[PDB]
Amino acid sequence: SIRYSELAPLYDTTRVYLVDNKSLNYQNDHSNFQTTVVQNNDFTINFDERSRWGADLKTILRTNMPNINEFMSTNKFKARLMVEKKNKETGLPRYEWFEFTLPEGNYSETMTIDLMNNAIVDNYLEVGRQNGVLESDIGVKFDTRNFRLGWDPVTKLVMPGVYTNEAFHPDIVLLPGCGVDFTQSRLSNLLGIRKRLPFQEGFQIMYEDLEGGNIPALLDVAKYEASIQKAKLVIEPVAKDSKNRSYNLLPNDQNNTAYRSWFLAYNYGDPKKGVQSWTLLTTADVTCGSQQVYWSLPDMMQDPVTFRPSTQVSNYPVVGVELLPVHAKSFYNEQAVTHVFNRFPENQILVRPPAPTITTVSENVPALTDHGTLPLRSSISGVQRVTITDARRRTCPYVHKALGIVAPKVLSSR
Amino acid sequence: SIRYSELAPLYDTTRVYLVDNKSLNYQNDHSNFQTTVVQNNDFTINFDERSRWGADLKTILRTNMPNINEFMSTNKFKARLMVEKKNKETGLPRYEWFEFTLPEGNYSETMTIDLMNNAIVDNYLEVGRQNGVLESDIGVKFDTRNFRLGWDPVTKLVMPGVYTNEAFHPDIVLLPGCGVDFTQSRLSNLLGIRKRLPFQEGFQIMYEDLEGGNIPALLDVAKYEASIQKAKLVIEPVAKDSKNRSYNLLPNDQNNTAYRSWFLAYNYGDPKKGVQSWTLLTTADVTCGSQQVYWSLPDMMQDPVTFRPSTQVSNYPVVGVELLPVHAKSFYNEQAVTHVFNRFPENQILVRPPAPTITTVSENVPALTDHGTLPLRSSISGVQRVTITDARRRTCPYVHKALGIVAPKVLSSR
Amino acid sequence: SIRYSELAPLYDTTRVYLVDNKSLNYQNDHSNFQTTVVQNNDFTINFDERSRWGADLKTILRTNMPNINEFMSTNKFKARLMVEKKNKETGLPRYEWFEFTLPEGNYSETMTIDLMNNAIVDNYLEVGRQNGVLESDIGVKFDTRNFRLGWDPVTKLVMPGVYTNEAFHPDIVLLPGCGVDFTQSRLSNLLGIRKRLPFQEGFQIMYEDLEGGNIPALLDVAKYEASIQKAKLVIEPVAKDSKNRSYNLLPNDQNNTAYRSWFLAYNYGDPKKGVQSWTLLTTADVTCGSQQVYWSLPDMMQDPVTFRPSTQVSNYPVVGVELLPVHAKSFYNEQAVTHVFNRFPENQILVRPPAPTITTVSENVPALTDHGTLPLRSSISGVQRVTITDARRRTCPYVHKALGIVAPKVLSSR
Amino acid sequence: SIRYSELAPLYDTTRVYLVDNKSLNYQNDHSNFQTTVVQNNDFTINFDERSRWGADLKTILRTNMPNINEFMSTNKFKARLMVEKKNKETGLPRYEWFEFTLPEGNYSETMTIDLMNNAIVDNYLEVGRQNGVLESDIGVKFDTRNFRLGWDPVTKLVMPGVYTNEAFHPDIVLLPGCGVDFTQSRLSNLLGIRKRLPFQEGFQIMYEDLEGGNIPALLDVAKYEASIQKAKLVIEPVAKDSKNRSYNLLPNDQNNTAYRSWFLAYNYGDPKKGVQSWTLLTTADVTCGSQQVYWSLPDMMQDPVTFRPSTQVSNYPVVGVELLPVHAKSFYNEQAVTHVFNRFPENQILVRPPAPTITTVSENVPALTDHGTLPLRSSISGVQRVTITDARRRTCPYVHKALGIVAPKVLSSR
């Protein structure tokens, strides 16, 4: 016999609506959307004892969050880079870890990468180009091709003049003494390079693992298709393409070059030896992979089997664990059919990484989820406080609206 | 009366969250995502006896897996090919089974095939072109046309100069003494050529079944539409197209040729005789068909009706069997409206197989599935171990995040 | 108290997984995917009596089937056609029913039709063009326009020189003494011409019902827009368009022609008189309409209210009736923005029927369906046999994988 | 204890399948798909008394219906129009309500409208152009622009020479003494002009409400951008555009014109005065809005709380009320990136209304719905009769296949 004191007991199963939009006077500041809402939406619901009152907990979780958000570390990625070329002491270049940041905004796939190899170009124009770096030693440069296709193993070059533009998977492209870090960050699932043994902190794809990859050097089709004029062969690889930038082709064998990619080194490399055995190749998951969204009602809902009845932004008794309602769509890219991302328009390695045929992008579907019956505090107060917390128990500042219908009902006696 | 010892019994139905993200200190290495997670997320849940405690088991299965992955054999396909042309002993070409591998990466349809007939071109440039193969005898070459359309049965040729570019279904195109194998592999459902009596190991579409197919030879429209000049007919089929490569037109009847396709031989052939009666023609299913994902909680959940309470990466008591959450989308291809895949740009048979109008591609939908009530170990330990295993009982190394809410509740007494 | 004999009774609700992938040794041949799978997946489950054991039956039905498949009659359609022109006896053309077949393959909309009026062109080039048919009397020719738009009822012609290319609904286009049959077939729902009183076998849209339709004859805009030169009107309809083919314009009124379409005759015709009153106009449903997929477990599941406990590929006790998991998608066609289908490029009636703006195509969604509780044989054997049968009780040879979790539980006593 | 008489009682919950495809011998004619199907699919199910047998009623409702169908009045719309110009008696034009009809066929958005202002062009060429109407007085003409944008309120014209082509919402465009009617019809939701107080029969948007709207007259940019030649202003509006048709610009103020649209008059007009206060502006809903589909089993299912146990095509005891399974999709139109709809290619008002960026179109999803438990006749006969009726209790002649699994089970005793 649920009661409300002096409003006629409406016994047996009822409902109560932890609404949100309304009473927006005493929960300003203390807000975001870990709100403290009210019931009795007129202008202490003592449940009937002698019955362990349970409650169904439907909800609505219309979230709102870009795929690149400095809340959950996603717009940062520590990347090494050649800072100084031929310093005075020790005639040898110098490397210093830089920590990059790219703008926020719910970005599609082929733009996030196309933004990555623009960030690690600014910290080349900023602190680097003024010293000695000669624009061919940019270092790390995210790309998304498979450089070794037209590679006939009679000459070991790449015959069709230029690398192929059909983008397969994204991948890193390094240089002697570089590399990236993705721990203390998470712009890896977006790249889709997540690591076997995915725990064990540390993820540093630096050019001591990638070797064995080594993208091949392009063949000078301005000689191959020009020497046959003299015949009707000079399979000389290219180093100085227009706007002369040496591809850093290693000198002991000029049929190869540096820029030892991460792909190829996970394909044309060596299993249980090369970059295999701790690097997978999952899909270009843009929606940050995923995160839980630990729902929480410190009152009304009793507690899970073993939670600390505490008071803090964290340590709330979690009740219900949806997903972060972000469904990654996928649209058939059309651009496949002068700029600022494609800075170098001749360097066949540094050119803009062509867009993958299936451009993915995050979304926001209002997950009208559900949670099974679960016990009630048997004495709901006139004021409750919903709260939406991620993994690391911070209150999610991107939820746009939550509800939380609650249908009480009996479960047992006494 | 569920208890936790000295934390006040919260009797009747509760919930317990086999989370994953967190305690990432004693399950490194022993990880992937057949993790060993913990409850009591503060910083031995003895269930109440006298009641066979059951439990609902919702879950979340945000997977992450490309459609071409050497985990489940999918990037390999044993294919025969003409290795040596006119060897010294026995003046007759030689055939030797090769075993191919194509790069990983969540590939769309018209690129996987467009990659197949690039792999079996490398092992022509590698070990083959140096000996005697004259580029017209590539052997197997995956395609996706229906060569016999403009085939007016008064001359039995193919009138409109060239084969038609409207891609219907993918299909194989062979040569006297070739063929493919797809057992010990699975790049067949992707081709959509799965075999009647789909068990019974062995699937070898070699050119002793395809005959009766035999794509027709193109008519020399440079004579038909040139002899009428002399008239206002010479229906002479073509053998030497620009960059002279003989279509291997069989000599006893020059109105036909070799390259006996697999299509046509499942259409313009013979029922209960030709390639019919053990080859279907299912849709170009790219998502590897499908696989189960045997969920498993060796503790908490008792066991199925008859499982071995064992200890091993395999033999776990399976509980719940979702699908591999890979929903194959389908986008209206646009390319229908110099390269490296289209190596030969004149050979009307070897040209790049035009893309099907509906390009399909795999995806990854987070399957928030469900499983009915099922008994509990009646004494959950403080540490559980979720685990996600495929068919062949290996732990799936591509799952990206799993959860597994568990709502206990009574089922009976004693 | 469910038992398994000498493996400790795991009393109360359990589960049992009629898996499929595995034991692939004694169900080869006897396969397709009406398999005979096993439980006890270690390497006679006597349920507890005194309780009418019921069972939930979830399942997974990852099918795999093109929209044009000679299994369910869909790639055939008996079509009449003018075989002989002016035979010796009785100076009058002769008509003989032909039975056509088009290739298989999961075909989109505007290609199936574009294949239809290619089949009934081969059996014009094959047996027909050699006799007397003069290419303007092809007979039936599937199309998808609405020929009577620019038809100003002051002259009753079609002013804008040519018929309009905006494709509305598909429709048939006949000729004096032709017609089609679609019984003993089903390529009608794909055309979307299904018949009122859809039972009552027989569906023959022959040119004795279509009359009253009669597409209008085009106006010679090479005279209308040329006589005003002589003025600044000769509304003479056209008969001989380039490559002279008479539109078969009937001689008593030259402001009309033959080719009496099926559309127009279901629009600009006569209700309760013309083709109305037994022909609808449903959507261009490509997914063969739909079919049931009678699930069946001859053991485990008792039987429906009144089934014959028989033994045969048919007569299985059906349990659960999903749909054929084929969801017809719909993509905005792009081609709207020399060939072989568009054989005649001048004949304004015989030209390639322009593609509808919304191209539909079949798909294959893995229908993770459900079925309510239903009784159990109370003595499951160690070996069961799932089986998937269509309407006409044949075992579907296109299912690619089935599962069938079964969660037993009590329903009553005794 | 459910029985079947002499086939062994299969007591407790069973199932029974009101299938459809099969017994197609005694339900021809009496068909459509309000069929009369049979159970006992071998070749009087007395349920057990002493228990008010209830039954779950799942179903399948694979419908099939175009968005323009003369079944539910949707292809008609009474529209007034200027029939006679300057008749003999009373030198003043004459108006007479016409009743239009457009062809059927599941039509997309920007074609239905593009068909509307083609119907009300035929009944201008038919009965109208022969008398006196001078093609500039077509009257009603459906459009989808917002004519007043480049309307700088210093001259009150429309500066950018021509109206803007970015289509916003569809809208009507009238003329002194015209208007439309949409009662006794329903091609309004498709236009998206549904009326506040949506009951109260009558919906006549005639040019006595639209005034205050009055689209503005275009500025002669052949003078404005030509008088500055004489200067380096003559803001003279245009009346005679090429192929001279006066825009019916009202003479007292030549900075305006007639063709008083419906948009603008619901925007740049007057709230609680103009077309506001009884006209909304809902989305361009193409799927006829929606309709119920009153399921009905005159036997098996008892009756609702208060239905007439009658016998008629109507008055069936309704059981279950799904939706008409028509899900309106939405595709990004591409045409935004000589004809017959765009008859007048110069008249800036009469030109083809540019297509909205989001082209919507109906579909047909097989709604595998559900209905809660509901009582059974406790004596099912061997022959039942499913039936699918719309609002006005006619049997829907567009359903393509229905099923209707029925799972009986107890609800109470006696």
Image: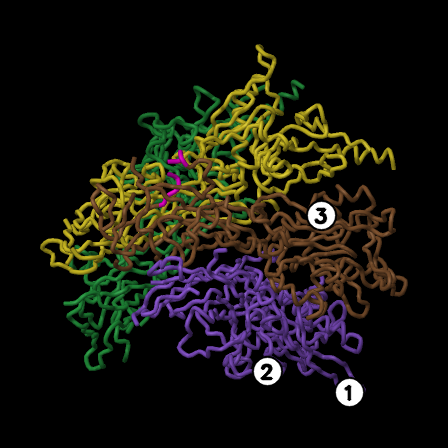
Chain colours: A green, B yellow, C brown, D purple
Where is C225 relative to B275, above or below? below
Q: Position of residue C16 (x, y in %)?
A: 31, 47
In the image, which residues are magenta? C18-26
Tag count in the figure? 3
- Image quadrant containing the C terminus of chain A: bottom left
Nearer-N-terminus badge (1/2) = 1
Q: Are marks 3 and 1 in contact (CB under 8 Å)?
A: no
Residue under circle 1? D91
Residue at label 3?
C98
Q: Mark 1 lies on which chain?
A: D
Task: Give the alpha-carbon distance from disc 2 to disc 3, as whole Å.
Answer: 62 Å
Q: Magenta: predominant secondary structure element?
A: loop
| Residue C19 lies within the magenta run | yes
Name the amino acid, label 1: Gly
Q: Is mark 1 on a helix, strand or loop?
A: loop
Q: How crowded is mark 2: few (under 14 residues within 10 Å), some or many (20 or more)?
A: some
Question: In the displayed structure, would residue B131 be above or below residue C356?
Answer: above
